[PDB]
Amino acid sequence: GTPKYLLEPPKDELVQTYFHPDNMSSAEKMKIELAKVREEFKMSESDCGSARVQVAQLTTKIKHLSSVLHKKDKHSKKGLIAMVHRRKKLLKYMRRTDWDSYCLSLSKLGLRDNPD
Amino acid sequence: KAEITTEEVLKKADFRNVRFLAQFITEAGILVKRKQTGISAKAQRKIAREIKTARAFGLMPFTTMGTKAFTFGKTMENRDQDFEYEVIDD
Amino acid sequence: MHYMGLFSKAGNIFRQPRAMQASNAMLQSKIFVGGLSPSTDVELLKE
Amino acid sequence: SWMKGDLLSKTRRLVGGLATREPVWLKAMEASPPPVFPRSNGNLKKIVLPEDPYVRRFARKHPEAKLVEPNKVSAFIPDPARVYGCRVLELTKNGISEDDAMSVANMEYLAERKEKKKAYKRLKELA
Amino acid sequence: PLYDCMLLFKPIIRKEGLIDLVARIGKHVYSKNGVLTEVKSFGKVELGYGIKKLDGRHYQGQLMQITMMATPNINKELHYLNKDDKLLRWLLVKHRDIKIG
Amino acid sequence: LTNSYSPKKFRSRHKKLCFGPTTMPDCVVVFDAERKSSVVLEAAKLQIPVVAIVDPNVPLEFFEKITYPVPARDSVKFVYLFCNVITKCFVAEQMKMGI
Amino acid sequence: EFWRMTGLKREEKKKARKKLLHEQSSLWIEPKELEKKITEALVDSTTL
Amino acid sequence: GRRILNDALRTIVNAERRGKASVELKPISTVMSSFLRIMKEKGYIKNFQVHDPHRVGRITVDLQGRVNDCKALTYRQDVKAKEIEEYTERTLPTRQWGYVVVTTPDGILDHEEAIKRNVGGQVLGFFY
Amino acid sequence: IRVKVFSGDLDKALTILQRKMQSSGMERLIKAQQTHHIKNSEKKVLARKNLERKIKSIDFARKLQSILIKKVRGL
RNA sequence: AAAUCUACGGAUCUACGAAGGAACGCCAAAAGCGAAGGCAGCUCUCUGGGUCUCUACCGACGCUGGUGUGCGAAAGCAUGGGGAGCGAACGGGAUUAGAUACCCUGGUAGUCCAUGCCGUAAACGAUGAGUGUUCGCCCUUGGUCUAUUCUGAUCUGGGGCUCAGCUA
Ligand SMILES: [K+]
Ligand SMILES: [K+]
Ligand SMILES: [K+]
Ligand SMILES: [Mg+2]
Ligand SMILES: [Mg+2]
Ligand SMILES: [Mg+2]
Ligand SMILES: [Mg+2]
Ligand SMILES: [Mg+2]
Ligand SMILES: [Mg+2]
Ligand SMILES: [Mg+2]
Ligand SMILES: [Mg+2]
Ligand SMILES: [Mg+2]
Ligand SMILES: [Mg+2]
Ligand SMILES: [Mg+2]
Ligand SMILES: [Mg+2]
């Protein structure tokens, strides 16, 4: 009942080039990059849904979509506008809740201040 | 009737398993409905999509009107042996 | 409530009556067509 | 009519004000009023027994088993599954592992089946 | 991602032509930084109808399958197979965990 | 009951001819589970008490007009038991007046 | 601690996938073993 | 508070009309507990119990079939101690039966007690 | 659909061909062929009328089969 | 009912071959998805949203919304392609008292593609969005848990029937 691959020695250079990020899809690359940017902005160690974490992820998604999305595709630009307005709502919450987190988010992500 | 189950369909349904997919076409070459096999809607969707992909690839007939009936493994040629007959009766 | 919960701790008192079990056996996809069941009712069931 | 209340209260209110003559059944209804029962929240609780999981397999166990109703008996004489569940409830009642209790109930049921079979054989012997 | 490339060669194409085309596609994958995990052949198959080309009509074909792990852009530059003269049909599909045979 | 004084006519063997009651009843005891007759509706219209045995699937419209519900399944034993209690109670009351 | 217990078992599942891919790597194709394996597959020629 | 107060009161009336025995209210509030205490004192509900009042509250109320309608006002309504009776003659649908429950510095009272204590405030609602 | 005739029995071959054209479903599609063009706004109306007719036939066959199966099995 | 039309320069019909355009039979529908308009052959790439489970995070961050902004069947308009079938306008043959129509025969714009404009429909469930509560029965889409071999339970949308209640 032993399969044939359990006899020959495994190959290390092929399994090294198997996981090169040119061989993975854009959704997997986006998952890895969002998991990277969550860790910089987390407050606690298990924190994944606080306001500044969501703002960082939304900014990454907006910057990706605003370049990738086609002009003729109008069904996903509505979702992009929804992302923009949700980010505005979260920033509006942070500006009156936590001024430290508001200033940290604006300075690190390079956005502007609006009381309007 | 022939017993087919949704799990069996979901494990076997692929456009390279033409022998298994030939259960779900009639003599006219058209697709069997769901109500006469009892499988789920997901199973029917998967079966129909795989038969369409196989038809585009060329392994299965689009229609069998004007041609012989499709069974797996033998040619769809219109040879001289398609209409062999008998003369000793006359 | 007291007595019915006592008598549940006894023999099999939750036994289906004959009429209900017979209706269950009467019941046990779609149906026969009208032009088929009418032919059956035209040939048979005239007795 | 447009009066409110049930039969006794509506009739009592009508006959108090000299609208209708007194019916005969009014006095019997006053002496024996209809029953009343408290509010119930509309919820029926599904009655269950602790022996239910052991009864379950008992149709797989000893596969199909006894039937004492077609054999119209009485709603008090237990039905195989019921006696098997009672034994394993009081059996396991005393700690005894669950599967070991199932085995020792299975063995005694089969010994009872052998005892019944030899009873029928001696029935044929004295027949 | 993980792809299966299915190719239907014409019935008169010979073993050297099959090896030449499959080696060309493999060298394409190696240049674009991919891994070839399984090559297999189904021999001669029977078609449900006559596939029609410039030469004539064909009723049997040779089936080859190559399993690869390549770039997402692999199907865009596998488009030179549409103008191939040893090929009847070609199809690149994603990998499915279904036993074949 | 709502029209107990309407005329009747003799026709044939029929299902036999029967007039209404001369006296209005004071109580109606019903053994109708398939609801074949309008007796509950007529007694509710004419303000007469109704003693009847109620099924679990009785409609609200028929239930609200029943004065004395007896919740049970009308098996032969329970119908006999019901009628036996009724008959024994009535004859025990009748004996108290010397009759 | 419940989050930590879930994060290890998911990391546990990912690693055993990589190990199974590693021991399955012994049957992949080198560029210097391309044509040999093509010809051997043509020799095998499995059923439909 | 007004949205959840009217929510619980309409739940109570809707379940009264179905002839039920108990109702469960969640979310709850101290104003709602005091309103229910006034209803219990006037005899429109039999009993009520409050569970876990400092983390996640739930209130169980036992009904008897005596309350016709409960309203909680969804707007601000001021009242002085000398306007209570004239306001009551125009708020209740029957102008005789029913109680207007106001909140005061002295606590949450009904309209008959607040006349005796001579203190006004915000009208919360009424039941009749 | 081709049917071979054996021993010169044309009626058996024609009956077999008719039944095979029936059970392959091709007779339904050969009757469903339209002579004119119908818009989608009329396809919706025709499908709705088809559904109503089907529901009426389902009720008829349900009631007929129930009153048959009450009598036939010893009742 | 006919005629116009088309055919002895060989039509219709029959077998094989070539070109080109549009739409995707069976599956298949009281199914599915989308805010609405809408979306049907198959393979790949990129992307929007949704559902279920969690002893995971955060902590009222929510609902509606004048002025504004965006999307928006079909027909139509501007520039460049394409044009099989259908077909406003128009030519002809019939019908009629007349027939600028219905019927027949040809057939341009258009329907199709790329980039823009307009911003309307019986854009209809003739029913604005949202929150809480209210007796059940029978189907169904996608999950999850339990099963005791055939089933139960709980979410999620879609349908049929109904106690109350409401309705001229
Ligand atoms: K949704
Ligand atoms: K909003
Ligand atoms: K209805
Ligand atoms: Mg939907
Ligand atoms: Mg247009
Ligand atoms: Mg143009
Ligand atoms: Mg025309
Ligand atoms: Mg004209
Ligand atoms: Mg034309
Ligand atoms: Mg309008
Ligand atoms: Mg519409
Ligand atoms: Mg609005
Ligand atoms: Mg379900
Ligand atoms: Mg639902
Ligand atoms: Mg009503």
Image (tube, rainbow, N blue to C red):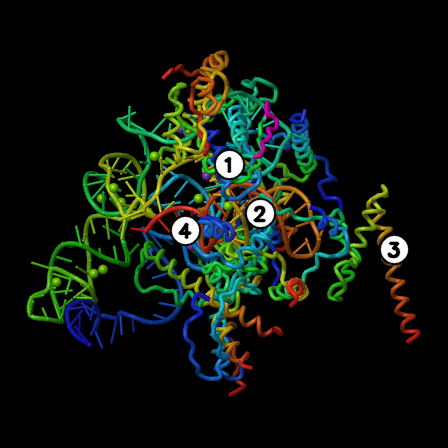
Q: Position of residue H108 (x, y in %)?
A: 49, 22
Q: Position of residue B85 (x, y in %)?
A: 52, 79
Q: Which of marks 2 and 4 is in front?
A: 4
Label ID, residue I5: none
Q: Name the residue under label 1.
A: H12
Location of mark 3 (residue): D108
Q: Do labels 1 and 4 share a chain?
A: no
The answer to which of marks 3 and 4 sits earlier in the sequence is 4
Q: Is residue B1 above or below residue D7?
A: below
- The chain containing the residue under callout 3 comes to D
Q: Which image quadrant for residue H37?
A: top right
Residue that label 2 marks: E65
**Distance between the alpha carbons at the discs numbered 3 and 1:** 58 Å
Residue holding disc 4: D2
- Discs 2/3, front: 3
Kindly report the distance in space between the C-alpha atoms of the residues bearing marks 1 and 2.
Answer: 70 Å
Q: Is mark 3 within 8 Å of ligand 13?
A: no
Magenta residues, start to end: H46-55
Both marks 3 and 1 on one chain? no
Residue A89 placement: quadrant = top left
Q: Position of residue I50 (x, y in %)?
A: 40, 61
User: What chain is tagged by disc 1?
Assistant: H
Q: Is residue B80 visible?
A: no
- Residue type at mark 3: give it: Glu
In front: label 1 or label 2:
1
Q: Distance of mark 2 from mark 3, alpha carbons?
A: 63 Å
Q: Marks 2 and 4, how far apart in space?
A: 87 Å
The answer to whether the residue bearing label 4 lies less than 8 angstroms from the nearest atom of ligand 15 is no
